[PDB]
């Protein structure tokens, strides 16, 4: 039921820069039940953020996450070449479960 | 012993009803009459002075966990005996009595708890459980779980899921 | 510490497929394992999830009548059964569960399987 929108569709910035992503919802979502995933071609997805504010163990601190209500965002401070991938936003508080559309970052 | 075997209905495992038999010259004349504390060699001649009598309904395969000093889902969360057990653990099957057309749902067994149980202890409280951080003020379904699950006890399964009644007398001095 | 999933399978339309997600430590430990599908280049799409403890389950309305998630405690196995395969289902299937050994659980879904390719 809940519809998530991810923007921008594509990003083109050189390594080292700062990128920002927005995950927008359609109804109130508890801030303790949101997460982000990273996907590279052919590999399994990776967990990045749980609860929208707690970074997963061992992940670089350059990642950051905040938001509340019906709109959540992800920000990465210092980008590097290996980070070029597609990130999916998942709200995982209310059944039925739901994912995002996807984004792309390159240069 | 006329009140704790021929009873029409038995209690669940998440709870259980016992008694305080006393002042009666127990006719132990009275199937797995497995006794641990004192063997029936002289069970008909004793000076115990105080006896309890619990009651439980459980699946056949889980009966082994009743014995002291063993681990199990129902022996580490519902009913655990002390290491110095002094009693007997009687048990038979109730395949054609407790089983019912389409099954019986009245029996339950606790599935989750904060910590293990101490001997001869019970806790009856149905509340949401489980978490890392527990901001579960409301009632939900992710990491906030209903603690009890109901047995199936269908009208006919093969041996191993059928209902066994087990009575665990706890002698004393 | 990882998830094990069967190899690729081949099926023709109308049949049914069974996919196994085998883990370690699931028994005696709470573990909410979900199921996610992903076609080539498409967005991830949710399917189902099940609690290894109580058997509680929930399915997407769309995938209702077509998905059956079954549990096996003794072997610590999880079964995802799909019936009446359609060409739209041809995709990769992942099983994900949260790190759970100490009774308590890591709230987020962190472990993810290697994936299985099913084509019809």
Image (cartoon, grey):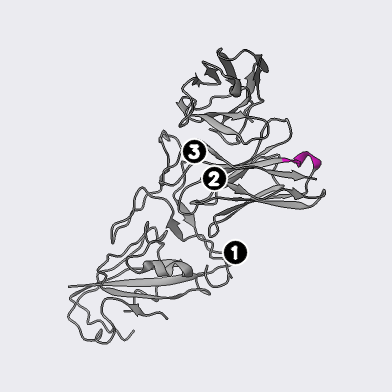
Q: Nearer the viewer, residue C108 or B1?
A: C108
Q: Are marks 1 and 2 on the same chain?
A: no
Residue that appears at 58% across and 36% down: A95
Residue B62: x %, y % from top left: 44, 66
| Image location (x, y in percent) of residue C116 | 68, 44
Residue B8 visible in the displayed image:
no
| Left or right: B113 in relation to C10 | left
Query: Are the two marked residues, 2 and 3, in contact with CB atoms closer than 8 angstroms?
Result: no
Protein chain holding label 1? B
Residue named by callout 1: B102
CA gap between label 1 and label 2 equals 39 Å
Majority SS type along the magenta span: helix
SS of the residue at dot 1?
Answer: loop
The residue stretch that appears in magenta: C87-91
In the rendered image, the vertical position of residue B4 relative to residue A3, given as above or below: below
**What kind of element bears circle 3?**
loop
* Relative side of B48 to B122, left or right: left
The residue to which callout 2 is attached is: C2
Question: Given this view, does label 3 or label 1 mark the residue nearer the observer?
Answer: 3
The lab-note entry on whether marks 3 and 1 share a chain reads yes
Chain name for mark 2? C
Q: Is C47 included in the stretch rendered in magenta?
A: no
The quadrant the N terminus of chain B occupies is bottom left
Dot 1 crowding, Cα within 10 Å, few <14, some 14–19, many 20+: few
Question: Residue drawn 40% across and 48% down?
Answer: B126
Mark linked to residue B140: 3
- Image mark for residue A21: none
Q: Quadrant of residue B31?
A: bottom left
């Amino acid at each position: 039921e809940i519809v998530l929108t991810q923007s921008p569709g594509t990003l083109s910035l050189s390594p080292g820069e700062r990128a920002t992503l927005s995950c927008r919802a359609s109804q109130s979502v508890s801030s303790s039940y949101l997460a982000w995933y990273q996907q590279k071609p052919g590999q399994a997805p990776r967990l990045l953020i749980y609860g929208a504010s707690s970074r997963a163990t061992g992940i670089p601190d350059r990642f950051s996450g905040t938001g509340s209500g019906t709109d959540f965002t992800l920000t990465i401070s210092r980008l590097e070449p290996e980070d070029f991938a597609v990130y999916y936003c998942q709200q995982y508080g209310r059944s039925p479960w739901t994912f995002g559309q996807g984004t792309k970052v390159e240069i | 012993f006329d009140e704790v075997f021929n009873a029409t209905r038995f209690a669940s495992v998440y709870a259980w009803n016992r008694k305080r038999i006393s002042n009666c010259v127990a006719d132990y004349s009275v199937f797995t009459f497995k006794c641990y504390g004192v063997s029936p060699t002289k069970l008909n001649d004793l000076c115990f002075t105080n006896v309890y009598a619990d009651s439980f309904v459980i699946r056949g395969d889980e009966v082994r966990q009743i014995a002291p000093g063993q681990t199990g889902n129902i022996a580490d969360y519902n009913y655990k005996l002390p290491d110095d057990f002094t009693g007997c653990v009687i048990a038979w099957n109730s395949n054609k009595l407790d089983s019912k057309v389409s099954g019986n749902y009245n029996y339950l067994y606790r599935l989750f708890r904060k910590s293990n149980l101490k001997p001869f202890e019970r806790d009856i409280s149905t509340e949401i459980y489980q978490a890392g951080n527990k901001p579960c003020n409301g009632v939900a379904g992710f990491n906030c779980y209903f603690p009890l699950r109901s047995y199936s006890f269908r009208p006919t399964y093969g041996v191993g899921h059928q209902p066994y009644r087990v009575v665990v007398l706890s002698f004393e001095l | 510490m990882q998830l094990v999933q069967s190899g690729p399978e081949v099926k023709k339309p109308g049949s049914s497929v069974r996919v196994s997600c085998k883990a370690s430590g699931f028994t005696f430990t709470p573990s909410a394992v979900q199921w996610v599908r992903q076609a080539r280049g498409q967005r991830l799409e949710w399917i189902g999830w099940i609690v290894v403890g109580s058997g509680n389950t929930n399915y997407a309305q769309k995938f209702q009548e077509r998905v059956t998630i079954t549990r096996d405690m003794s072997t610590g196995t999880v079964y995802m059964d799909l019936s009446s395969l359609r060409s739209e289902d041809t995709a990769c299937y992942y099983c994900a569960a949260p790190h759970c050994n100490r009774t308590n659980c890591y709230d987020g879904f962190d472990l993810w399987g290697q994936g299985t390719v099913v084509t019809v």
